[PDB]
Length: 46
Length: 50
Image 1 (cartoon, chains in turn green, yellow):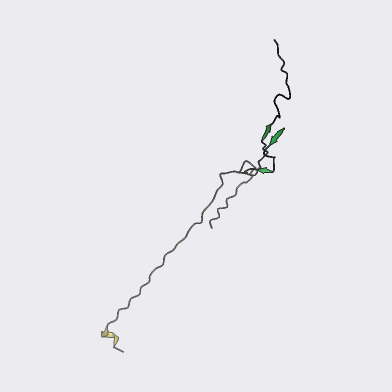
Image 2 (image 1 turned 120 degrees about the horizontal axis):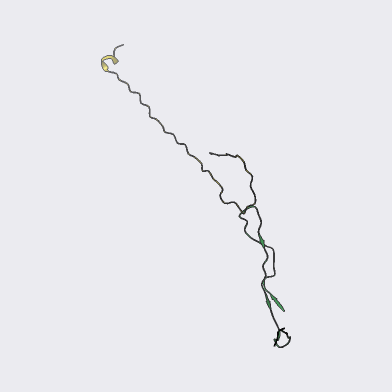
């Protein structure tokens, strides 16, 4: 699962001129119910 | 007012909120007031003579 915290919205910032600076933030985290549920292989020698 | 509206050539861009700018204050003008004085000199030796 992906724990989301910020939910990007209409964010604006300063101008200090004729331009219009904009940004988009996001705070996200991973969640796994049980580590021993899934599995991974790693390619290598030996 | 001291508008100081020297224009020359003005062609700007959106270069991040130009900060230099410029500003003129209001200049002051203050005069003075003079005191007038006119004296009179008369003696009784001639003030009574018609």
